[PDB]
Length: 324
DNA sequence: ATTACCGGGCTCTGCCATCTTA
DNA sequence: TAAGATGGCAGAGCCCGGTAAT
Image (cartoon, rainbow, N blue to C red; front, side):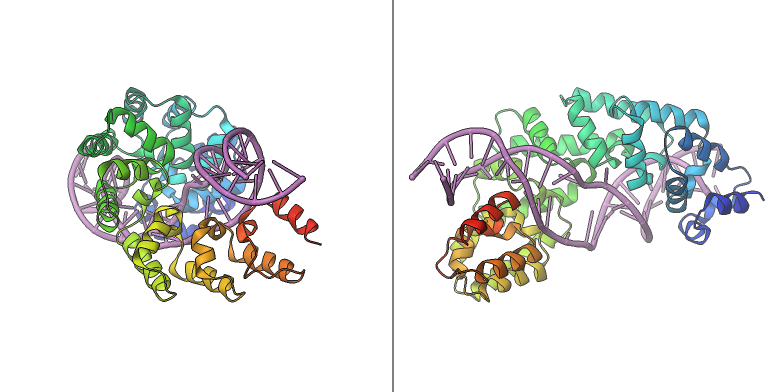
């Protein structure tokens, strides 16, 4: 009865909430008052609280003890109340979609038992909070899968391959083993690729390739291949290009294409680009903005060393002064 | 004095489908 | 037998500067 009214004064988007979890609006008891007071107690703003509830209404069904207990468990990982408030604003659901504080505590123990430092748990929690709402068994599967994958290739100690990969790729525990498997086979298939090279790639520059959704890597690579082929790059040149800079796989087709075109329209050859792949780091705005500045001064661009297009503001802007 | 090489910083959902559970 | 709990999916970069090399 009082529910709909309280939510209103709280500032909640009631229509959106209703549509997200209608089941919660058919409960005869709810704790929206306790929740609001609880989150206020911990620093949250009035609008954040409304936003949280609007996106994950079931939040209002937790008790002060559950909330406080779960919070205190998050405080075993993150050092301050404010850090947790920010994570909850950014995704409420990782905190509130489970009321199983025992599982949570077991997750924490299991992760520690994998040999992860607190700083690494903190990095997980802050950037992939949903790791902590996974069931223990779910996090176990991924770790097991990774060990198995580690030794299925040539890794001298899998236990340490796991830590390297989890530190470099903090999102790995919230991907399915299906997705990750498929991205590893994509890499092994498309490139060479001996286990030793595949390890390095996977632990290092290619680490987040493992988090790409189904077929998105294959599709993105296909586009890179087409686009470079069309410009007179051989397949070997294309592979070498992508392995030297796997981040290029993350770009959307159009973004990669527009980036290439915007450079070559200034007479930068494809060869200049693929031999200095880091120029593709800059956004299109930054590239266009810098190109204008440089042509707008003496510069050729066809013969210039284009590495500067991806330098820091400070280093770029200094070289530009000198150039005039 | 200037560029290259290379790794690190920041990275934090919101939905639906399919079970459990009471 | 309806909610709650859980798994799983699409989504689609940019920037900085330490330190080696020249």
